[PDB]
Image (cartoon, coloured by chain):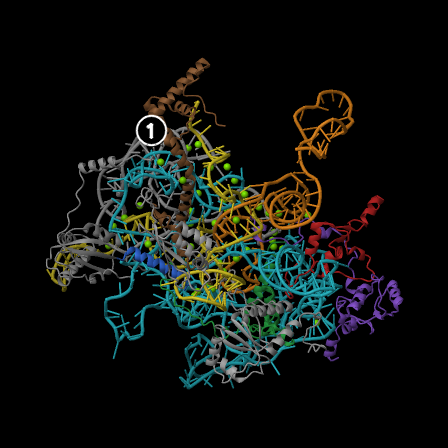
Chain colours: B blue, C red, D purple, F green, H brown, J cyan, K orange, L yellow
Amino acid sequence: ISRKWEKKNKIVYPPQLPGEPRRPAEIYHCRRQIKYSKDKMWYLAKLIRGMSIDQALAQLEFNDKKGAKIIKEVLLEAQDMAVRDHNVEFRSNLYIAESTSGRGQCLKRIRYHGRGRFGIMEKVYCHYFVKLVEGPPPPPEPPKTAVAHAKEYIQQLRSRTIVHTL
Amino acid sequence: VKKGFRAAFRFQKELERQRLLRCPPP
Amino acid sequence: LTYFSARKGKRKTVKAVIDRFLRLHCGLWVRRKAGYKKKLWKKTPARKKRLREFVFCNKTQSKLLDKMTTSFWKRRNWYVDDPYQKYHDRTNLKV
Amino acid sequence: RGHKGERQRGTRPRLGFEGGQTPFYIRIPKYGFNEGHSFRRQYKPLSLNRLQYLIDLGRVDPSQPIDLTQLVNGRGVTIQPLKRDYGVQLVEEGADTFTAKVNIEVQLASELAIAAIEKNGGVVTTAFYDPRSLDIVCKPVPFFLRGQ
Amino acid sequence: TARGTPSRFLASVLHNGLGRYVQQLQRLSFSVSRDGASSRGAREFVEREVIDFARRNPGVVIYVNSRPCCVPRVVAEYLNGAVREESIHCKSVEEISTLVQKL
Amino acid sequence: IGIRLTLPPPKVVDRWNEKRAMFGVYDNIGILGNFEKHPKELIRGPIWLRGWKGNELQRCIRKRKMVGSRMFADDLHNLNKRIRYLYKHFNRHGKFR
Amino acid sequence: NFKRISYAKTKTRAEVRGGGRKPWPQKGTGRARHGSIRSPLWRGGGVAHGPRGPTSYYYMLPMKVRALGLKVALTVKLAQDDLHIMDSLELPTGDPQYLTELAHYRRWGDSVLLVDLTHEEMPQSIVEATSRLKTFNLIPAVGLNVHSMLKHQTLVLTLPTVAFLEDKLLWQDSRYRPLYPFSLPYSDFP
Amino acid sequence: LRNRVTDRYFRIQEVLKHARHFRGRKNRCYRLAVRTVIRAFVKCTKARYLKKKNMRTLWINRITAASQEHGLKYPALIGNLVKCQVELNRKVLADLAIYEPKTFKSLAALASRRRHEGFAAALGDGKEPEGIFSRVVQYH
Amino acid sequence: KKRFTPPIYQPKFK
RNA sequence: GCUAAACCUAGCCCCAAACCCACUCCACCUUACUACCAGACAACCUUAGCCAAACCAUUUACCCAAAUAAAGUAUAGGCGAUAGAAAUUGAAACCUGGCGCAAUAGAUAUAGUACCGCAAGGGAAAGAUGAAAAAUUAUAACCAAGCAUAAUAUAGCAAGGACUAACCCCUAUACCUUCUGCAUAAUGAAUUAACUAGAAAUAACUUUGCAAGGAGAGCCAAAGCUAAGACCCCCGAAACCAGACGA
RNA sequence: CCGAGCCUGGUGAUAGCUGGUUGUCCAAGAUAGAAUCUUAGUUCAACUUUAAAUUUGCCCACAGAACCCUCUAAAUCCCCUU
RNA sequence: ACUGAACUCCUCACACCCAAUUGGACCAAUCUAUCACCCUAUAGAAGAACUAAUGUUAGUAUAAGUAACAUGAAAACAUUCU
RNA sequence: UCUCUUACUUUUAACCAGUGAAAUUGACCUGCCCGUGAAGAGGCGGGCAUAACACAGCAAGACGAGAAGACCCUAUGGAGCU
Ligand SMILES: [Mg+2]
Ligand SMILES: [Mg+2]
Ligand SMILES: [Mg+2]
Ligand SMILES: [Mg+2]
Ligand SMILES: [Mg+2]
Ligand SMILES: [Mg+2]
Ligand SMILES: [Mg+2]
Ligand SMILES: [Mg+2]
Ligand SMILES: [Mg+2]
Ligand SMILES: [Mg+2]
Ligand SMILES: [Mg+2]
Ligand SMILES: [Mg+2]
Ligand SMILES: [Mg+2]
Ligand SMILES: [Mg+2]
Ligand SMILES: [Mg+2]
Ligand SMILES: [Mg+2]
Ligand SMILES: [Mg+2]
Ligand SMILES: [Mg+2]
Ligand SMILES: [Mg+2]
Ligand SMILES: [Mg+2]
Ligand SMILES: [Mg+2]
Ligand SMILES: [Mg+2]
Ligand SMILES: [Mg+2]
Ligand SMILES: [Mg+2]
Ligand SMILES: [Mg+2]
Ligand SMILES: [Mg+2]
Ligand SMILES: [Mg+2]
Ligand SMILES: [Mg+2]
Ligand SMILES: [Mg+2]
Ligand SMILES: [Mg+2]
Ligand SMILES: [Mg+2]
Ligand SMILES: [Mg+2]
Ligand SMILES: [Mg+2]
Ligand SMILES: [Mg+2]
Ligand SMILES: [Mg+2]
Ligand SMILES: [Mg+2]
Ligand SMILES: [Mg+2]
Ligand SMILES: [Mg+2]
Ligand SMILES: [Mg+2]
Ligand SMILES: [Mg+2]
Ligand SMILES: [Mg+2]
Ligand SMILES: [Mg+2]
């Protein structure tokens, strides 16, 4: 058993200078031993990814799954600990930067088939990781138009030189 | 346990090399 | 031939080799041609004389007879009236 | 180990088996070569040349009667108590250039050897001893330490 | 293979053949043990030929730390800043001489 | 992974102890000792090998001949089985014959 | 190697408590082919080829070879200035401090093998001086070998001790055959 | 266990360091990485002749393209160059055709003149001139 | 004949 | 970074020495773990079998008296694969360890526990922070197989040659084996970590020592004798007997 | 799971039958046959592996190697020079 | 006419491409004696090396979130209905 | 039963919620024709073919999965009957 995600909230930074930017905050929080599947948790994390915290809560409140309420409570308690301890004033100025899933400790049981044989029932467990960063959420990457492809093709055709001689 | 010291020393040196490579000191 | 016994753990010999052959100290085994005493009425006297001669063995046969025996049968005996005493030592040997 | 089979599995016949074929040491009939070798009387050779050599070196003093214990102490011949040995014989190989003049007790002495010994003025005594007497005369110190 | 290791181009460090040729090697930090059977070659080298090697080219500085260790090593630094560290564990005097000459 | 992370403690050994500094004492006592006792009598250990080498099966035969009359039941059975196995492996199986 | 008794012993596939019947049929199920457990291929079986009983590496060298080795060791200790002949191993007060100070002043090294003679004829001063140190040892003239000499750096002998060693090493040359062991009273040999 | 293996991971890393840029399970499975590295090294060793042949064919194709652009062919050019006592391999010819067109055009003109002189000598079975640019130099 | 093999049950500790 | 990787002690095997023990009260021979009522009958016995002799019917060390040489000698033996003495010189009392190991090793064992059958019986993994857990602290992280971080982008046993850039250009028919010929559509394989497979005599080769003698009693010897080094696998069947159990 | 049961010991039974047999380099290295209740094995020929002793190994040439009625080829065996 | 190999040549020194098999040289984790203690040498021993034996054990992927699958309805939760 | 099948209900079928297999897997960036090879090629030669990724059904091939074939043959390996 290893626990290194809950300890990232204790990294103290030196005091900045007046000629330095604001630097956004980083809030780490995760739960352990959750009776759920890792694939569904990863699907929920992919549904979330980089969006606003309020939009994520709204999408999870109407999500018909088992871990939706769990992730909702995780985000709620993380926002609470951020506004109470991590020095956060605005409640709607947060966005999820990283959101992934892991795997928990498993056991073994029986399945009982239709003969003397049987199966290995492995109790699947998983976790859930999430990171909260202050400030407005970054806009998504816009798709490159034909001008970008044309410029890249021109650059590729201009970068080629003589080969296999001198 | 596995009795030895030279292989353990080489493994510790490799760990120190990986540490100094991942985190380059000033 | 039992390379290791169960009581002494030594090497045993084959008594048939001792009863049918005779090793000299030079490294030669004296044998006897078979059939020298049976059906002698249909054989020419030349064959009868040839069968009654002390014939030596070969190389692989001598090696086999030596491997079937131990170090006791490869010594040198000094009998009082040994008819094969002059055949123990072999002189005039040039590789 | 080569290819598979008995050459690799180790299940090989004993030394001398030719795979059903009659071996060489069986097709030959028996003969009276070593009938009673464990009962024949063996005698270690002893030439007059080696006796004169021992006398000249000093290991055999020609002032005392020489028998078996004197030859064992001088270490000129090796008398084995076992292997059916009834003493040491005499060899006339060193007939010429033999000047010793000393009595010697030999179990088996030939005519030429006795003649050559009597030429200088020696005495040859032919005696017989049982293997127990041989073992006694070879090493008398353990016989004295025995207690019999 | 070439698809697994990085490559470069063949060029001079600061055009030595055009103007004047300078010595690329700078320092040579040797680590010879005091007692042991693994630095005999390095000991004999420092005893007999290190003076000739230092007098051959004045632009190369030789450092002898003489630290009691087990594997004798040598540090060679150049003008560009590359540091190539090799070990002379159980080598003859001729081998070490050829190695330092190649360096 | 079968590699120990932390280094083992330095196993220091005093090379000048009792049996180390006094090794080989009273060895070869027959030559320079007017021949009183044989050097093979200074070997301390099992009684069935005090001055005798032998082979793997010969040692078992000597043990069953000397000490075999004062062992256990399971130990004697295991010794007999090992002797039978060595006999069947040396006088039936093998090579160079 | 002449005083080595390896007490290492590992059980085979027959001495291990277990393995009697046949686990699963060979033709029935589609598992691996096995006839009994406690095998060197299974988990918890015996060693296939390992130490079987105590192995004794007993072997003796000829007496002449050992005498020549002793003479060679003596020549090596004498040539390299590592042999100091004494007349009477005595000390004024008998203490390890004076002994090690004298050893360091006379330039001997970190170790020295002090050899006396007859064992019983040894003074108490040097005994009490050596009974408190590890490098200094007191062995009689009979208990002198080659390993103890090669382990130390120098050697210390005495005139009667070196005479005894010389005569015992020259007794091997110009002698008779063994024939019977020398433990007998003999006549000339004491 | 007595004096067993205590440095097996180092051998695994030494084998896997050559398989740090492969696709699939070959960069992680040692049992397959061994075979992959073996085949990779074998092909890298055996492809030297292939590389040499490819470079030679590329040089020949470049020379042929240059000769066709100038107004000649490849076999005639090679023959006229080997019949004028000038030893220039394919690499320098390709380098000139790519970088120095003036000397390549001069070589093509010399080759055409040598070919014309050879044709004239063959049709006349020569007698007297036998080519001005001919006349082989005798080295004794 | 009628060949058939009986199944084997593992111990109740895994 | 999740899954999960190493942290030594219960001790385990054989030596030398020593000979080792068995009711606190009740219950234990019937339905043992049952306080109390009328036929007393209960042991005294060649073991067998496998293998080998290429089968096998004679035969095959195992027999419980200390070493060795004799000697693997006389002998027994479908006289053959094998077995094997005796007579004889003889055999120095007393000292506390491992050139063995650390939980897939070493006894199976923390234990003869769970579990299987009415029954004899078979029978397996366990325990890791620390001086202060009455320090529930903040850290020490970093390596395998499985995962997200960071999915795919045309072409081809997954590889090589290469250029300024992954592909695009060319070449190239996985691994060990019974086999003349195997990737062949024959055999084995999902990986990682632990374990597993050449043990030895007579006769041979080399190197010290001594020498007509060598060798720490025994053995060999018309240049020999002693010592050392060097060498000969694993797993997988149907069958037979002996002692106990079941309608 | 009875054309003959479960457990233990003989037993690590035997088995010409199947499979496997662990790091590097270099050198040498490819098979006329006979016997066996044997061709799925074994033993002996021939070849291969080491260090020594001796001197001749290969095409060699004029010449030599009965036959018989009907032909009887391409070749072979001993062979100093080179 | 030209293209066209591991055949030949250019600078180097050349033991660095046969089945079975044989011979010669190095390599590393344990203990012991001798020197050093940021890790190696001289000598003795090995339970001295795993890409394979439907090899034994424990962790974990593809197959596969594939097949199988529960609870009669309303409700004050006091009840009612087939 | 067919000519010639059809009208409905349940199990079941397709999606949502979770426990969740078994056989099997050398790795796959996995198309077709002609020809060749250990004799039946998606990985060999020449051609044709080609943006990538899931869901819902059928079997034509991958000599596909389960049993070291029970049919034929070898075994100086067994057993039953007379
Ligand atoms: Mg095989
Ligand atoms: Mg075969
Ligand atoms: Mg057999
Ligand atoms: Mg027959
Ligand atoms: Mg058993
Ligand atoms: Mg079995
Ligand atoms: Mg075990
Ligand atoms: Mg048989
Ligand atoms: Mg007796
Ligand atoms: Mg255990
Ligand atoms: Mg166990
Ligand atoms: Mg990993
Ligand atoms: Mg291609
Ligand atoms: Mg292999
Ligand atoms: Mg096969
Ligand atoms: Mg075939
Ligand atoms: Mg296949
Ligand atoms: Mg097959
Ligand atoms: Mg398969
Ligand atoms: Mg009934
Ligand atoms: Mg077997
Ligand atoms: Mg066969
Ligand atoms: Mg070319
Ligand atoms: Mg060539
Ligand atoms: Mg070759
Ligand atoms: Mg082992
Ligand atoms: Mg091993
Ligand atoms: Mg492995
Ligand atoms: Mg299978
Ligand atoms: Mg495996
Ligand atoms: Mg499906
Ligand atoms: Mg369904
Ligand atoms: Mg229901
Ligand atoms: Mg579902
Ligand atoms: Mg092919
Ligand atoms: Mg086809
Ligand atoms: Mg295929
Ligand atoms: Mg089959
Ligand atoms: Mg047969
Ligand atoms: Mg049969
Ligand atoms: Mg039978
Ligand atoms: Mg029967």
Toward the viewer: L70 or E78?
Answer: E78
Question: Going by the picture, which residue comes out furthest to the top?
Answer: H124
Q: How many marks?
A: 1
Instruction: Answer with left or right where residue K38 lies relative to residue I2.
Output: right
Q: Residue at x 79, y 55 (%)?
A: C87
Q: Name the residue: 88% across, 63% down.
A: D111
Location of the C terminus of chain A by quadrant is top left
Provide the residue designation for mark 1. Answer: H97
For image coordinates 80% across by 48% down, the residue present is C51
Q: Position of residue J195 (x, y in %)?
A: 46, 59
Give whichever of E33, J39 is nearer the camera.
E33
Q: Quadrant of the N terminus of chain A?
A: bottom left
Crowd class of label 1 (few under 14; some 14 to 19; many from 20; radius 10 Å): some
Q: Is residue G102 visible?
A: yes
Query: Would you identify the image quadrant in which residue A161 lies?
Result: top left
Question: Does residue H58 appear anywhere in the picture?
Answer: no
Task: Indicate whether F25 appears above or below J37.
Answer: above
Element marked by disc 1: helix
Instruction: Give the quarter of the image for residue D135.
Output: bottom right
Q: Numbered disc 1: what chain?
A: H
Mark 1 residue type = Ala
Report whether the residue tagged 1 is closer than 8 Å to ligand 23. Answer: no
Q: Nearer the viewer, residue J81 or G96?
A: G96
Q: Position of residue I1 (x, y in %)?
A: 49, 49
> Percent from the top left, x then y, of residue A41?
23, 53
Is residue D138 or residue L57 the one in the foreground? D138
Q: Quadrant of residue C81?
A: bottom right
Residue at horizontal 54%, vertical 82%? G90
Pinpoint residue H92: horizontal percent, then vertical percent.
37, 31
A76 versus G138 height, above or below: above
